[PDB]
Image (cartoon, rainbow over all chains, first blue to last red):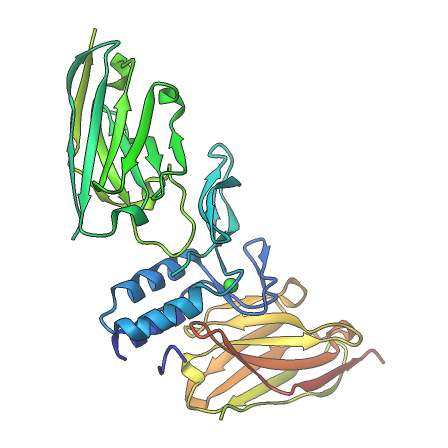
Length: 116
Length: 127
Length: 118
Ligand SMILES: [Cl-]
């Protein structure tokens, strides 16, 4: 569509494209550096995009867009969190749940996206 | 549209046991982690235990490890907290919580992971 | 189709300034996240600066305080104002248009900037 590259799905991509915090390929920000070949976003934007597509009434377009975005190999987002110590559950090559050292200050880190 | 219905609280003597249950409707139960939190009088709400959608991963607050056991039955859309060797300091309102829809990995002992909360069930442990 | 055309490159003495321009197809511009990259001699392409659709910016450490990215959506043009140029800024500069949901990238063929020391 105009925003994803018919109306409800298009509006999900619009909002996602206006994410306030993005990091281009090779960009350094927040003490991180994006080593992927495409832009990565804050996890809250990716979270809201995922939920928007899942709840969209244009269910067929949303299904294609969600799968395309989220199920690409090695997809990640960043956010501020206590230092990550491990993964509690992995499925299909993705961390579902992680653990942290709650006693150390929060720092920006990288997190797996969920499969759609 | 999801609703959480808790039960199993009550007034028990110290050393005793209870089993809380929380049944959840409105979406596919097995896709989401479920957690238990508690709030004692005058204290902040705190994490107690949580379990992943598959049941394969569980987490417990340090003060309840070895005494409490969380489990879930995805065919009944229900999560359980078996509470043994109860202490006076376990007195609190216990709240079931259901993980929000998210597009990235989540931490089970963070309150922000959960978007839906039960009204709670009172557990009082007397000595 | 999409077209990204950089201009404004050239030779300048160290301590001088240049302003690069990247004109795009107006169809897309206000929607795109925009960035400048550069390729110094004998190196890979590297990120310099990003500007979001709302105009918020981030810069590489080596250009902070010297370079300014800006966008004029009405003119479908991205700018890079380069002040206090140094010989280490000699490079081909490329503009990049990004569409976040489709993970689409468009690139200009780049404009040469040479900073002589004298
Ligand atoms: Cl990614």
